[PDB]
């Protein structure tokens, strides 16, 4: 059908004006290179989400009760039918297959539901179907817990695509992050399914606390993996053995993926440097001033980095070219504000245990202000005939 | 010594060999009518009229007093009119040697002429059209004077000629032209040049300023931004080295000098070199038997800011000093965007081509992609050496804003200064025409 | 003195009038087109609020508080008329003695100069001050912080709308609908400080 | 009850204190100045009615009006003022009329300027010379279906200070006019009586003013000749309300009293040597006749001229004797005509249909340089668009297309 | 305009408006307080279990069955005063009759406590069966106020009702859920060592336990707020001495 | 005829075109009880203020016109507030500040300045009623969606059973917050300007 050939093939056009020779880069290649960057993170996330579910299920149930539970859920009996096993010694194959059966429905639902609105708008306004949804859909499907209902994911992606992105004019015209706008819609509308201890480990009847919110209770000594009984170390939280969403669990994979797109120039290193500087400064100020009743005042920078969705946000979600600043002088300020706001929401605000998604949305509002400040300074320098 | 840090030396194949050789005999010239900004002609000649050299072809209605003259003596053959009866070109068949003769001056007396006496001779001879005023790139008004004239004297365009080769043949004419410009300026003459040596004029008004770096260093806009910033209250004239040689020869001999040394080079040329030609020649018979078979695009100027030479426009421009030929790319390719290209060029590091240092590409006319919205990954900031906000200025131009574009600095720029920004745009936007529309709106709202 | 710093930061960020209490939208959505005009109006609002709150505090403490003038009498039902009279007189003074007699703010203050009187933000600030029972210095700091927060919000909206010159909005949502949706997105983003105990 | 008296007293005291503060502040600052404006330096006339506010409310009260039209608000922009001292602020509504260039030298509209402080003006000389008059009507005879020519005589032999193509601002006091006594020649009786047009009537409660253009030329001094059209409901929608002032002027008879207010003008002829092209329709014969007679009988010009006219039928043409005599007298001036739908008894031969189409197919297509000659258009707004499109397709600049229109 | 006319116009308008405004705001001053008292009386009746669907009978039922009474926290004994018009909020606010709690003992995070409190005794004739104790503490978003009705033995709770809170509905605003409030009946507040034995446990409490109460699911911060509220108000600084006197009899 | 009272419902809607009274729309639309009470209160206050201002339109000096109008409007709002506290105490406890903020409602001042000062008393009263109806239309329409989707109720009555009470509906938490009001008003404006193209704004 024509909907496939027009995607695979290049249009085969020629230049007719101005620069008769053009650069080989294009939006399709940019979006595809970003889409491929999250593949190692997604694969390790699927593996870890299978492993956590298997471990929690084995810790809770055993024997006949375990068989009754395994025969009552379609993820478990599909994993058992496809050759996998739910025993205590399941291999990486089954640990990845269970995560796949937990993640693929969410990705398919998000893709189809968002693409419907994308096609509808780009057909009504007589455009050609753009790209960037290939990135938005995968980021949204990676930043949600494995147990999120499909009817909630559909509404989240609907809000993110329609209200936040498509109303303003489509790709390259919006001012806010679409994936994070949808996630914030879900976060504020249905907070029982995106918070608590029941949503991170995809096991039936198992309640396991957030690795980030286990710190606010008792400090570094309170970090424990109740699924297996072991304690979470920095190496575990860095490699990505902690419970969490599909996407942001692994940090080594995120660094590996984001190094390529930083090298290729798609993602700016200025925003990443600003985020790092802000986080380090604020999270060292908090340690220096100290506190007695708050246990997050003593969390250092290298523990802020590994836990939560900090790495995923900083690498893949804070570097959105459209939402970020357009000035090399304002990109540093944008990154510093993002890092400072994330650390502040983590430490001082008690209602929300994680604040990267809200910090990015807050800095998206004030990026144009930084752009205006720098451009006004440049104009005032021009008026002195020195520019 | 002024060093430019940002830019892009375009690695297109077929670089010319800087040796001047005689070109093909040219039996037809033309003087275009779509390259002069805001020029509304009043034709003084008709098809079949016989014209001498330096005899006026048409005047201006928006710029009274400026006269455009015939490069060679012959018979007019075409007055081609485009859409809405716009003047595309006036074709003259060179069939004679008669000419109009002007006054002659000793080489010593050229530094003390009156400005009005210089202006009258320049306008009568037709060399007044060599100058251009930044902003708006219009031909200078007959009675206007500026205190800064920027003799380019350097070439950094892709597949461009080396001015040191051309000037050393005409050192005396170049010196005399510099003396005339120093007597005419009333300010200073900024003779931009590379680190190599050039003939020197013994005048205090003339300054030699040395530039360096990649392509945008050899642009009159960059020279003005770095030596004499321009605005609505400060206009500066611009001129190249060959027109300076023409001015010197005019004031030394009394006859207009209509020779040229252009560089015929490109990916699809058998033997790139410098060919001695005539002003406004016919490219269709200039490039015959010099091109490999197949479909080709012949350009009158650099591939970054040239003009396609097909049909009525298939003649050399006034301000262009090189002819570039490259193949036409029309075929599609399956999964071309996903290929880890070794032969593909990009300022970004997303292709395997950039790893191989020193590679030269056989670039074609394809737009590698399709028209989309602008996602500013940071390509314009890599290739803009000026003190501006590029990705804000281009968004201002695309949105149609004019006053804010002026505030951001659109006046100092020309269509030739946004060629690299158009080149490195993932959205495949053409910014030169947007800037020209913006400047036309600014001029009208005067 | 840390109490005043806490009050200032709380009023500016934790309790931003424009995007946490949502007062003054009738002008917040209508005048926010250019940063210059938005900054001028924010300065005017800052001045009016800073002068209005302490005077109302003095009057309420002196005569309108229950049992404050004569024991057994309670005149707390003149609050609305007294507050609106003080605000209106101050706005008239600002418009007529200082703003236009001195070098004027041409096109920075137009139809919206007499609209400060009916700006809901100032009346809301006075009412909240009455509820919280501040002292004089706390009232001054509260007024200044509220004004600065309102100016910050309006200037951020103006900057966003200036960035939105490149957008392509549907004809129905041109201008006002898109302004409402943009303000809703900004309010969604401004919920980071919701649970802070400052 | 004791709280009620306290509340009443405190309400009164607080409101009185606020009002007194406002009044005292006003008394401490109000300039209370007067005569803050000088319309020019040389003339002694530097007096107005108001110390500030809007500018017409001070000048028109003292008798100065560029054109103090009804309502104001710059809906037509004839209230032209030039300023050189005072506030330089520009109303948002004034950028539409004033370009930045004119803004630097201080050009604005009058119904937008607000006066508060001292200033001096540099008003053009035409303000100092315009005046009203007492012209009596001589003839108001009909010569077409909707076209009437009005002839007036100037009292005491004065000559209006006008140029070719101008217009005087006619007045019409309160009146009530009926169409019953209207009567046209026998040929126009058919279409006139098809709806009979006499049942119509107009109500005028206060004096009203519109403008008309002179069909005469400066060597016909002592007599004002105009081309007046009747304002009737459109034939396709007769239920549309009719026109008032045009009907009133139609009702004017010979020997009747009339008052003009003064001549104004635009659309003048350029002082060049290029060819002149005059194109028009409907009631547009007035400026074209004025220009033709000026250039030929008054200016003795020898520039090549052509006057292209379009009509509907042979019965719809007048001034034919005049234009034929002028063409016979002058070789440089040739005038052509076309009919939209000629009738079998018109005995018409030659051009037919739309005037722009006949022009393009007959003259300008074979013209060598249609971009150097000057065009003057004054006619129907629907002919305006067609002629503009044709000339722009031929490639004529805006400076060579000089047109006069009455805003559709 | 002239001052002679402007002052007269302003004075006449003020004299026209002020009588209306003052008469409206003074005539209704009785109803404006009856309506306020009705809400508290209805809440107390609901906590005590007496059914009164109407402001007509709420007044008589509260006047006959419920006897408000003041209690001194420091002495744990009754005080004589206008209990029916007491204002605990302003009493705690004023520094004249309040104690500034210190950090180590301000478990409920209320930062101030009144010197004398108010309790309500439910009785018929002159025999008392219950006593309603108003307790409050800090939650997550706002202050949470409640009435807890304990039996005359000083141990057994016969109902808990939250009448003022501002938590998130559906997540932490489940303190007003009848399914959650109805499980407090029969629970015991003290152990044999006179320690506060009420424990809001997470994830569910053993069925039939005399000291455990089911926590709010997904609302651990609000559950901790409730736990702090009870650990403070049942402690030494709250109704501790008063309940010590109560369990000995003579309530 | 009823053009004055019927047109400002859609033709000249205050919130949709004039951008007047939006703060109360964002605030009090969470529940239909408060929305309807606010609609009635603003209707009565606007109508009576317009009536009195038109009655005394001749004898208002320019210098203290704002004070003269605010005296009347604040007196009306004080009377309304006392009546609400006396008879509708449960509702009045919920509106709180946005009952005293009726004075600073921009609709009241806009209709007092634009129409009341220069129109006859009865036309002013009719125009006030019409503007109040046009405002209440938006108030109740937004409140319908907000209440129904955020609490599964209408006027305090049960319509959609809640999951916490043994039903099937899981309430949306955004409807009880402010951004939902912004989104609903934006989409209302979109639909109104789609059905009535004459109100569409220009690109320039
Ligand atoms: C500088 C200048 C010179 C001019 N010179 C001439 C000249 O020489 N000769 C000439 O004939 N004209 C001339 N005009 C045209 C001018 O407009 C004349 O006055 C013309 O006769 C129109 O009459 P009026 O101004 O009385 O129209 P008005 O009575 O002001 O308007 C009535 C017209 O509007 C219509 N109308 C009224 N109410 C409505 C309604 N509710 N709905 C729809 N339609 C309605 C009527 O049917 C009628 O067409 C000139 C105009 C200008 C600006
Ligand atoms: C790519 C790397 C770029 C960043 C380079 C390094 C930046 C770090 C700067 C500060 C160095 C120390 O940073 C941090 O200091 C604080 C003390 O100040 C230490 O803090 C430690 O001791 C304090 C003592 O009061 C405890 O309360 C705290 O819980 C504990 O972590 C952290 O363990 C250390 O990580
Ligand atoms: C938007 C939002 C609002 C919340 N509101 C409350 C609340 O009002 N009360 C509460 O106890 N928890 C609330 N929570 C949840 C807490 O933040 C915290 O995650 C939870 O109380 C801990 O659950 P657990 O320790 O029982 O696993 C809210 C969470 C979100 C995302
Ligand atoms: C480095 C990079 C990061 C991106 N991040 C996001 C993101 O977080 N969310 C999203 O919806 N799109 C993202 N996109 C896609 C696209 O840029 C985005 O939709 C724009 O905001 C256009 O609406 C990203 C693209 C790139 C190149
Ligand atoms: S009426 Fe035209 S400017 Fe005043
Ligand atoms: S209507 Fe303007 S502040 Fe509320």
Image (cartoon, coloured by chain):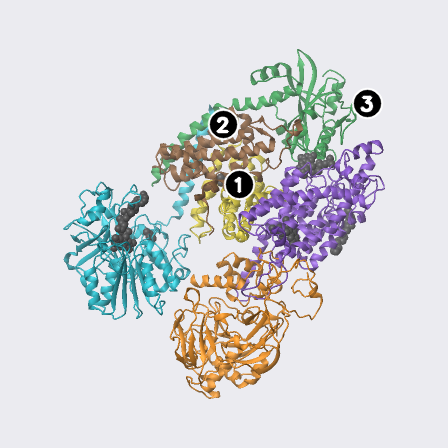
Chain colours: A purple, B orange, C yellow, D cyan, E green, F brown
Q: Are marks 1 and 3 on the same chain?
A: no
Q: How many marks?
A: 3
Query: Where is residue E131 drawn, in percent x and y?
Result: 69, 19
For residue F187, the mark is 1
Secondary structure state at the residue bearing disc 2: helix
Q: What's the distance in space between the residues labelled 2 and 1, CA to CA?
A: 36 Å
Residue under pointer 2: F82
Mark 2 or 1 closer to N-term?
Answer: 2
Q: Which element carries disc 1, helix, strand or loop?
A: helix
**Could you give the CA–CA distance between mark 2 and mark 3, rounded to whole angstroms?**
54 Å
Residue B104 lies in quadrant? bottom left
Q: CA distance from mark 1 to mark 3?
A: 64 Å
- Marks 2/3 in contact by CB < 8 Å: the verdict is no
Q: x, y (%) of residue F60?
A: 36, 38
Q: Residues within 10 Å of mark 2 (few under 14, many from 20)?
A: many
What secondary structure is marked by label 3? loop
Question: Horizontal placement of E30 versus F117: left or right?
Answer: right
Q: For this rendering, which residue is in front, B23 or A40?
A: B23
What's the mark number on residue E192?
3
| For residue E190, above or below residue A163 | above
Pointer 2 chain: F
Nearest-to-viewer mark from 2 and 1: 1
């Amino acid at each position: 059908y024509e909907a496939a050939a027009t995607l695979f093939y290049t249009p085969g056009l020629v230049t007719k004006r101005s620069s008769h020779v053009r650069d080989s880069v294009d939006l399709k290649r940019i979006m595809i290179m970003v889409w491929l960057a999250v593949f190692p993170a997604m694969f390790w996330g699927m593996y870890n989400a299978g492993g956590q579910a298997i471990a929690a299920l084995n810790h809770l149930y055993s024997g006949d009760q375990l068989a009754a539970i395994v025969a009552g859920n379609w993820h478990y009996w599909l994993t058992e039918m496809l050759g996998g096993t739910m025993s205590s010694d399941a291999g990486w194959g089954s640990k990845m297959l269970l995560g796949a059966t937990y993640f693929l429905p969410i990705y398919a639902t998000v893709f189809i539901v968002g693409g419907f609105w994308e096609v509808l708008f780009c057909m009504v306004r007589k455009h050609e179907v753009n790209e960037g949804f290939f990135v938005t859909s995968i980021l949204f499907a990676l930043i949600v817990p494995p147990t999120l209902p499909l009817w909630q994911a559909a509404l989240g992606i609907t809000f993110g695509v329609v209200v936040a992105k498509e109303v303003f004019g489509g790709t390259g015209r919006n001012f806010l992050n679409p994936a994070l706008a949808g996630r914030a819609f879900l976060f504020f509308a249905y907070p029982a399914q995106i918070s608590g201890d029941l949503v991170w480990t995809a096991a039936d009847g198992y309640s396991g606390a957030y690795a980030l919110s286990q710190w606010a209770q008792g400090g570094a000594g309170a970090l424990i993996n109740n699924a297996t009984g072991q304690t979470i170390t920095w190496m575990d939280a860095f490699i990505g053995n902690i419970p969490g969403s599909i996407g942001e669990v692994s940090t080594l994979a995120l660094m590996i993926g984001a190094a390529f797109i930083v090298y290729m120039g798609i993602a700016s290193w200025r925003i990443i440097g600003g985020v790092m500087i802000g986080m380090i400064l604020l999270s060292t100020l908090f340690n220096v001033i100290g506190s007695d009743t708050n246990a997050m005042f003593n969390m250092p920078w290298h523990w802020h980095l590994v836990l939560g969705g900090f790495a995923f946000g900083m690498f893949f979600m804070a570097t959105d070219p459209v939402s970020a600043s357009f000035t090399n002088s304002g990109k540093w300020a944008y990154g510093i504000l993002i890092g400072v706001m994330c650390v502040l929401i983590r430490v001082v605000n008690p209602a929300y245990p994680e604040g990267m998604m809200l910090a990015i949305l807050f800095a998206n509002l004030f990026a144009p202000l930084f752009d205006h400040v720098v451009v006004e300074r440049n104009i005032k320098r021009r008026l002195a005939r020195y520019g | 010594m002024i060093t430019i840090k940002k830019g892009l030396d375009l690695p297109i194949a077929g670089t010319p060999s800087q040796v001047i050789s005689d070109g093909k005999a040219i039996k037809k010239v033309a003087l275009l009518g779509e390259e002069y900004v805001g020029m509304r002609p009043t034709m003084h000649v008709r098809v079949g009229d016989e014209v001498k050299k330096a005899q006026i072809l048409f005047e201006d209605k928006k710029n009274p007093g400026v006269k455009f003259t015939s490069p060679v003596s012959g018979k007019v053959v075409e007055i081609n009119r485009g859409a809405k009866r716009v003047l595309q070109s006036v074709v003259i068949e060179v069939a004679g040697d008669d000419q109009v003769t002007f006054d002659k001056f000793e080489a010593n007396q050229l530094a003390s002429l009156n400005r009005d006496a210089i202006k009258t001779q320049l306008v009568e001879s037709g060399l007044w059209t060599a100058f251009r005023t930044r902003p708006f790139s219009k031909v200078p008004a007959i009675d206007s004077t500026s205190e800064a004239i920027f003799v380019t004297a350097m070439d950094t365009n892709p597949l461009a000629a080396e001015p040191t080769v051309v000037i050393n043949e005409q050192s005396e004419a170049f010196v005399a032209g510099l003396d005339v410009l120093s007597a005419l300026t009333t300010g200073k003459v900024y003779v931009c040049k590379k680190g190599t040596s050039l003939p020197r004029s013994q005048q205090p008004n003339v300054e030699e300023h040395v530039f360096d770096g990649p392509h945008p260093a050899g642009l009159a806009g960059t020279h003005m931004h770095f030596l004499y910033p321009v605005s609505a209250d400060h206009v500066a004239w611009s001129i190249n080295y060959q027109d300076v040689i023409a001015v010197g020869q005019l004031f030394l001999t009394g006859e207009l000098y209509t020779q040229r040394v252009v560089s015929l080079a490109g990916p699809v040329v058998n033997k790139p070199r410098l060919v001695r030609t005539v002003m406004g020649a016919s490219l269709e018979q200039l490039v015959d038997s010099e091109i490999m078979p197949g479909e080709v695009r012949i350009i009158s100027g650099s591939v970054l800011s040239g003009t396609k030479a097909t049909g009525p426009h298939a003649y050399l421009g006034r301000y262009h000093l090189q002819v570039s030929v490259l193949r036409e790319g029309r075929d599609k390719e399956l999964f071309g965007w996903a290929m880890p290209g070794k032969n593909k060029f990009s300022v970004t590091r997303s292709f395997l081509g950039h790893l191989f240092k020193g590679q030269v590409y056989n670039m074609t006319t394809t737009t590698n992609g399709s028209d989309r919205s602008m996602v500013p990954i940071g390509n314009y900031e890599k290739v803009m050496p000026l003190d501006m906000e590029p990705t804000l200025l281009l968004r201002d131009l695309c949105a149609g804003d004019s006053d804010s574009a002026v505030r951001l600095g659109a006046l100092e720029l020309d269509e030739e200064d946004l060629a690299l920004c158009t080149f490195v745009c993932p959205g495949k936007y053409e910014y030169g025409q947007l800037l020209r529309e913006c400047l036309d709106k600014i001029e009208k709202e005067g | 003195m840390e109490h005043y710093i806490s009050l200032l930061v709380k009023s500016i960020f934790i309790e931003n009038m424009a995007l946490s209490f949502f007062l003054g939208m009738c002008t917040f959505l209508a005048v926010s087109k250019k940063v210059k005009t938005s900054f001028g109006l924010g300065i005017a609002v800052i001045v009016v609020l800073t002068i209005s709150v302490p005077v109302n505090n003095l009057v309420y403490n002196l005569v309108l508080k229950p049992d404050a003038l004569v024991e057994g009498v309670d005149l707390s039902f003149l609050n609305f008329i007294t507050f609106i009279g003080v605000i209106a007189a101050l706005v008239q003074i600002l418009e007529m003695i200082l703003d236009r007699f001195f070098p004027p703010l041409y096109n920075a203050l137009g139809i919206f100069l007499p609209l400060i009187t009916v700006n809901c933000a100032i009346f809301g600030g006075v009412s909240f001050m009455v509820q919280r029972d501040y002292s004089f210095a706390e009232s001054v700091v509260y007024g200044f912080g509220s004004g600065v927060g309102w100016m910050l919000a309006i200037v951020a909206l103006a900057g966003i709308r200036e960035k939105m010159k490149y957008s392509d909005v549907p004809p129905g949502l041109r201008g006002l609908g898109i302004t409402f949706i943009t303000a809703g997105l900004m309010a969604l983003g401004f919920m980071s400080f919701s649970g802070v105990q400052l | 009850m004791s709280t009620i008296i306290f509340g009443v007293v405190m309400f009164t005291l607080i409101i009185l204190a606020l009002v007194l503060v406002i009044l005292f502040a006003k008394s401490k600052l109000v300039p209370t100045g007067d005569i803050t404006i000088s319309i020019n330096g040389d003339p002694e006339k530097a007096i107005v009615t108001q110390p500030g506010g809007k500018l017409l409310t001070a000048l028109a009260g003292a008798g100065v009006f560029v054109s103090s039209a009804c309502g104001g608000g710059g809906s037509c922009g004839q209230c032209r003022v030039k300023i050189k001292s005072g506030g330089g602020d520009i109303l948002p509504t004034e950028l539409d009329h004033i370009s930045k260039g004119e803004a630097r030298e201080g050009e604005r509209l009058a119904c937008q300027v607000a006066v508060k402080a001292d200033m001096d003006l540099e008003l053009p000389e035409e303000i100092f010379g315009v005046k009203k008059w007492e012209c009596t009507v001589i003839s108001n005879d009909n010569k077409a279906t909707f076209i009437k020519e009005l002839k007036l005589a100037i009292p005491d032999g004065e000559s209006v200070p006008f140029r070719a193509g101008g217009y005087i601002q006619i007045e019409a006091p309160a009146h009530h006019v009926k169409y019953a006594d209207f009567d046209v020649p026998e040929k126009y009786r058919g279409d006139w009586d098809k709806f009979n047009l006499f049942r119509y009537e107009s109500k005028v409660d206060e004096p009203i003013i519109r403008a008309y253009s002179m069909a005469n030329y400066p060597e016909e001094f002592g007599i004002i000749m105009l081309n007046v059209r009747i304002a009737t409901p459109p034939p396709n929608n007769p239920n549309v309300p009719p026109g008032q002032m045009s009907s009133y002027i139609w009702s004017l008879k010979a020997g009747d009293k009339c008052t003009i207010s003064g001549p104004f003008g635009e659309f003048f002829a350029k002082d060049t040597d290029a060819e002149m092209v005059f194109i028009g329709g409907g009631a547009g014969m007035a400026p074209m006749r004025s220009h033709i007679f000026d250039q030929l009988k008054r200016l003795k010009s020898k520039r090549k001229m052509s006057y292209w006219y379009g009509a509907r039928s042979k019965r719809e043409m007048f001034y034919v004797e005049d234009f034929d005599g002028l063409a016979a007298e002058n070789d440089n001036f040739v005038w052509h005509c076309a009919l939209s739908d000629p009738q079998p008894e018109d005995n018409w031969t030659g051009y037919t249909g739309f005037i722009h189409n006949v022009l393009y197919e007959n003259y300008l297509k074979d013209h060598e340089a249609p971009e150097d000659c000057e065009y003057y258009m004054c006619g129907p707004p629907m002919m305006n668009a067609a002629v503009i499109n044709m000339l722009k397709n031929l490639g004529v600049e805006e400076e060579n297309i000089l047109l006069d229109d009455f805003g559709g | 305009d002239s001052i002679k006319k402007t002052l007269f116009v302003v004075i006449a308008l003020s004299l026209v408006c002020s009588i209306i405004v003052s008469a409206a705001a003074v005539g209704l001053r009785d109803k404006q307080k009856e309506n306020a008292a009705l809400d508290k009386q209805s809440k107390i009746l609901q906590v005590a279990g007496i059914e009164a669907k109407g402001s007509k009978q709420i007044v008589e039922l509260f006047n006959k069955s419920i006897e408000p009474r003041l209690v001194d926290f420091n002495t744990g004994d009754f005080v004589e005063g206008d209990a029916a018009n007491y204002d605990q909020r302003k009493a705690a606010k004023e520094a004249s009759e309040s104690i500034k709690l210190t950090a180590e003992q301000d478990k409920a995070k209320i930062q101030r406590r009144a010197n004398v409190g108010v309790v309500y005794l439910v009785k018929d004739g002159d025999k008392t069966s219950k006593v309603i104790l108003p307790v409050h503490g800090n939650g997550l978003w706002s202050m949470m106020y409640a009435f807890v009705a304990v039996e005359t033995d000083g141990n057994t709770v016969s109902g808990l009702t939250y009448y003022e809170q501002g938590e998130t509905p559906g997540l932490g605003g489940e303190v007003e859920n009848p399914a959650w409030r109805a499980q407090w009946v029969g629970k015991k507040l003290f152990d044999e060592n006179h320690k506060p034995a009420i424990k809001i446990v997470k994830g569910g409490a053993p069925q039939g336990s005399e000291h455990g109460v089911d926590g709010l699911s997904g609302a651990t911060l609000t559950s901790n707020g409730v736990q702090n509220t009870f650990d403070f108000w049942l402690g030494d600084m709250g109704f501790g001495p008063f309940l010590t006197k109560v369990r000995d009899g003579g309530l | 005829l009823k053009k004055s009272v019927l047109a400002p419902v859609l033709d000249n809607n205050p919130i949709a075109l004039q951008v007047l009274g939006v703060c109360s729309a964002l605030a009090v639309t969470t529940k239909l009880e408060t929305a309807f009470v606010m609609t009635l209160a603003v209707m009565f206050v606007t109508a009576l203020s317009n009536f009195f201002v038109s009655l005394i339109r001749n004898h208002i000096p320019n210098s203290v016109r704002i004070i003269v109008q605010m005296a009347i409007i604040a007196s009306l709002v004080i009377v309304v507030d006392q009546i609400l506290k006396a008879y509708l105490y449960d509702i009045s406890k919920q509106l709180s500040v946005f009952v005293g903020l009726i004075i600073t409602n921009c609709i009241v001042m806009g209709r007092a300045e634009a129409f009341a000062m220069k129109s006859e008393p009865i036309p002013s009263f009719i125009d006030g009623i019409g503007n109040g109806l046009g405002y209440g239309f938006v108030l109740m329409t937004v409140g319908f969606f907000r209440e129904l989707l955020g609490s599964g109720k209408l006027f305090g009555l049960e319509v959609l059973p809640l999951i916490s009470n043994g039903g099937w509906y899981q309430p949306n938490g955004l409807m009880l917050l402010a951004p939902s009001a912004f989104f609903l008003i934006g989409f209302m404006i979109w639909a109104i300007r789609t059905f009535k193209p004459e109100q569409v704004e220009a690109k320039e």
